[PDB]
Image (tube, rainbow, N blue to C red; front, side):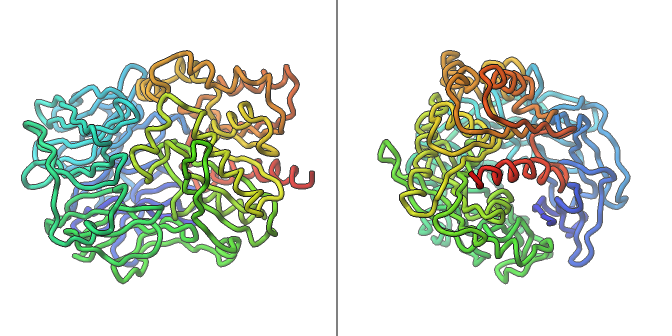
Length: 560
């Protein structure tokens, strides 16, 4: 079914959206009635637009999933007419923003990640970022942003539009989750500490980290623990979407706004009426109004794929270190209790299983499988402490917790059998759970998985090279003993390896040596290499592409 993410306004007050619609991600214009297409070809994403500008910056995969993006400036008045910003080699755009006079954005290549500036003079490199870095906001000649530069920690990075450059602002307390410039050009960020979460006023000149205060104190009472996203509206109001335990709240000047139960994010000022992008375990990402909650954009979701879940529960699991991992349950009406159960680990890992829409969680509970979507340490939304616990310890505690969700299930009386399923870092978890715990589960599905750190290293761009060092405390001896490939002499339960050939995140190269390894020590497994597919789905299809083989493998087990 169709999906719509909020991008922002342009054309004055013509809401800009993006839709996973008809087997393709397309940028869209919405004027309160009939959505209008912009892109010609299925795109991938659309650079954060700056309110009311008459053009859009499409982000296209010119490599077929490989993540090498080409930029096209599609004037909004002329839907379907595109200009490939040629003064920009295809690369990996992590994020950017367009102001209508010039485009800045972050790109990572073999050699480096840097903040780029495309204006009416040609290409310019603003600043070279340590590793994964994102353009949060631009206001004036200012450039506010985020960056994973050290310790799974997130930092505040600021640059310039003309002279460029960059100074990185840290917090001993915690990481940053999003920012947006204010009138005072002081970066209003959200400090996520091992503790809780709140706003701060990080000033560019000296880097003052004073606490930010809001008029209404709802947000200051919601006791947020992790700020999804935030940012000022044109009227001048600071839009803050915090959240705790998978659910979020709309706050304007502290002033809480009533919104559909689940999750939202970017909030906008369309025709002067607040608007965000809802998503719930049962409702797929969509664009609604607030606080009324009426949906402006939502795709025809069946009444059975929502009926394919008898219920949901946030249970808190007892981890080995006595840590409680906040887990997400999903009963599969099309299954009994206990019954077959699959442990669906979110990838990331700095992601999480919240009360939001998960296509795997749905299909799964639809396949007669209850689901367990634990927020192991490294996950997001549960404090800077739980997320930084993984750094340097990939495939350790988390796994344990990921195993503690498994533990729960059977004794909890809901699992008659347990299988672990995952993608990306989740695919990676399916591999450690199976190599480090050749028994916990009945079987494992790994997709766009991580099988060798040292190779994924020798096959990654500057973005990804740095990411690893971090998640392993800059030590090879981890990329060695925390890479399942070297632990293939110990796997016992079956395993399906779903993998996109062109994935440039989790390459296929090291994944094919893994299959070949399995074949040596003759292990029972099945491989799935999807064609011209990368790490994500820029089509409605490739959802089912790496989710069709899975279920069969996962149902073949069912019958012993």
